[PDB]
Length: 49
Length: 49
Image (spheres, rainbow over the protein chains, first blue to last red):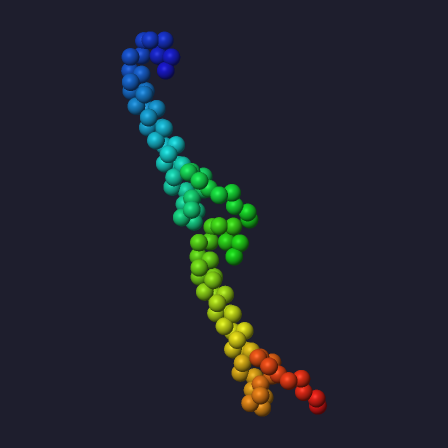
């Protein structure tokens, strides 16, 4: 996204690419329901095995 | 019932399991009627053979 410093006008597409990946860091953040009480997103309560 | 510390939500089932076993410690406590004056539950009067 240096873009050839200003030469890739289609950074816009890259921005969309970025947005997609950003959404992934929500999906992976969710979806890990080992227990219906999933691992690492939001609030996990520091459990004690 | 550590539950993987919080991961077994179905401790609830374990709780039921526990309750059942707790009830056993009443049934065995009763049901030992050697004499109609059973052994060990409630009040046995410290007899002298």
